[PDB]
Image (tube, rainbow over all chains, first blue to last red; front, side, top):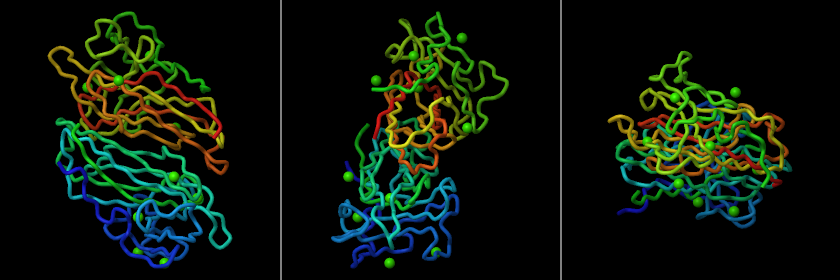
Length: 199
Length: 198
Ligand SMILES: [Ca+2]
Ligand SMILES: [Ca+2]
Ligand SMILES: [Ca+2]
Ligand SMILES: [Ca+2]
Ligand SMILES: [Ca+2]
Ligand SMILES: [Ca+2]
Ligand SMILES: [Ca+2]
Ligand SMILES: [Ca+2]
Ligand SMILES: [Ca+2]
Ligand SMILES: [Ca+2]
């Protein structure tokens, strides 16, 4: 009867960040970089595709609100042209797919706004949020929410596993994906929640 | 509510006279989406197939009549789960416009009951996609739980900005059988695409 599935660093609050609009340039602790098209290079520079965590606090240049949860958000920036592929965050969980269970995956998705060194961050690359069992995408929200620059909206993915499902007892996973279907390609995620209830 | 025209949007073509009679030919106005070649070039009644079927009084496979009209569209895949996907595709004449909210609605159905000692219980999963060109703008990948013999409505929404790269490409719709379970039979009906300023 445990209603929440544990997720590591689910609000990207690790690491703690003191300075408003300071961001890391390494994969967030507890997550891996999902990189099926090799858009994120092994050797990052100040100009490559990048990901990490950032502190949204009073005075932020990029949003019309604070973080949806805690201090930080997670971000994915892709430098390649629209259509070049996707990249994002992945985390395999310790829980496994169980039958007669409805899963609800909720994630806040954000659109970088404002300007950076007098350069507009307007535009949005699109997102996808996936619930996995093993390597199988059980359910996903592919870019259904329209999110204005500097704002956040909550995505909800749902999946019901029946006793006959082929992927029972495989490890659950979550992917948070930058679709790179537009620029500016900066995308935020926050407050990942996976909850369960009887089907 | 302002509709974008879609050909054979409720799979009512062809007319089918007999209850629970199904065609095994791709419905007029649609094409077979076949990225993993699961639907063979030379079809038999035992291979993967798509087509349309009449749901009327006396149906053995559903707990309701069709969501719309007489007919539903269906996709059946003979391969094992994990083998790939297949479904229906239709490229529209309308092209993607900026500052415009698109709402795609489609009823998705789960074959139920039995056909000659063989159970149709189980569900393969579905995905409903809105396209511009070859680009999937937005999609519902299997979020609805649909019991055997039942239908539910999937809603996909998308808004494009003036800087969208795919403006002026033709809109498209895909209705996909995910083959993530058996029995693999999957139904679609009543495709609606509506448009409004953002
Ligand atoms: Ca947070
Ligand atoms: Ca920094
Ligand atoms: Ca590195
Ligand atoms: Ca933006
Ligand atoms: Ca909001
Ligand atoms: Ca119909
Ligand atoms: Ca027939
Ligand atoms: Ca079924
Ligand atoms: Ca095509
Ligand atoms: Ca229903």
